[PDB]
Image (cartoon, rainbow, N blue to C red):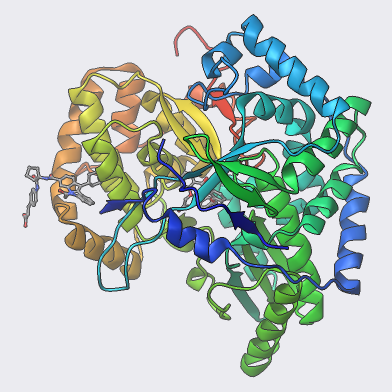
Length: 551
Ligand SMILES: O=C(O)/C=C/c1ccc(NC(=O)C2(NC(=O)c3ccc4c(C5CCCCC5)c5n(c4c3)CC(=O)Nc3ccccc3-5)CCCC2)cc1
Ligand SMILES: O=C(O)COc1ccccc1C(=O)Nc1c(OCc2ccc(Cl)cc2)cccc1C(=O)O
């Protein structure tokens, strides 16, 4: 069937930023017919996946538990209540939610309505490698449906992918654990070969059968009868497809592929990508495969069979994925160095700690992170990508010297160090105070993230070249600025001094000892690197469970 059909009604609105203008160009690419042919490898992998799902027991979340998971700036319902009413458990919100739930149990076939919208993302043009990227599309149900999805499937999408995929499930890893996983997998091979597989419009490649196969994996869970019916009903009425409405309420057409803004998007895409990839590994006869999957993002680390043989197996893997309705964007290329693999926009690099020991870390080209931070400094934004990049890329040269220095000077000038800000980690929203950054960093990357040096020449040059192309002052200027930022932070004591001492120890002439932060243990990060929730509409506020009086 067609991934999408359109009426003609426009997708209306609600260093460039992506707009609803370019939505017409995106529609053309994501609109096609799917031809999927399944085989014995696919059927075998599926049965193996279902046997592991059979060990999962999932709980039905209460209305209150589901309401607490709703982000405060989550789109309001078309039925007279918003995200604040949901979080406060107002009678109107709760009554509406309970009737939407009852309707999921009684109606098994009527397609649920969704809103289509062009996502606004900040990119960096540079007319040296083509032109501007068209806006991505976001398809999501009403607020009431979104709360019901959490009641029925929040525990499923948080527990099941790990039980099914094991160590291949990428969202269970902090950046430090992701690093450790890839390094260990690379070292486990006699002669390693690795590749990244990029699918062309993954959401659009997802067929109705893929969505039903995904439900067959969920149905293997021990579930409450009502959860079981809600999964069945949500699959038919929402997940498989349904009508699309623009921001103006006009009928835009119809979808028969994956919706980007449903709770099961990340889980479903990870399960589908893993299933198709593991099956294709068998068709291509790749030896001792190690996969790492985050939605549509796949990395394969395997045993090399020779330069000509690896190229042949990669074309075979591609032919199999294409048959499964997952053709590539860019053709995959075999890499024989771990650093040469770019997965989830990131690559492995090495540095040294204070005692000269090797430390592997994840980094990426810093153009987009810096362009986005520049946009966010210029105008007020709901999500601060700068904060997420400080969190995820804390050991990197660019995040330490530029992002930490720039944003801590602004927070110092605005006296906003204690003000909690929202950031997105694995598709989920987190309300974090900048003053908690040293404890967060120690927990995800280790105490060494504050003492890293001996960066590679390639990494230094990439960062340096990037600062030049963007008009950012050189690294020597940042060192000077960090010294004042650090001095002012130290003078304030408490968590602010810890920000000075730990985040800016790289800037001082004579470096400090740096002992573990005692209050880092009491930080509750149990909901952090568990699962992916892209378009899932998930919120968590950071908690410091059991505080000592002297901390
Ligand atoms: O010794 C030498 O040889 C050269 C010395 C030298 C060169 C330039 C400066 N610049 C400045 O002082 C000013 N800008 C900055 O001190 C500045 C700070 C952050 C900047 C950023 C980002 C960096 C990441 C966090 C968010 C801010 C960008 N740009 C920045 C400029 C340059 C800019 O204006 N815009 C962009 C656009 C895209 C990407 C980055 C930028 C402030 C007043 C005048 C301009 C200072 C010293
Ligand atoms: O790494 C990037 O360039 C963007 O990643 C981020 C940076 C800051 C804030 C959030 C993200 C993020 O959650 N990224 C994601 C991801 O990363 C997987 C990974 C893990 C650790 C590192 Cl160091 C790099 C990549 C896998 C799948 C989906 C997403 C998502 O966008 O929701």
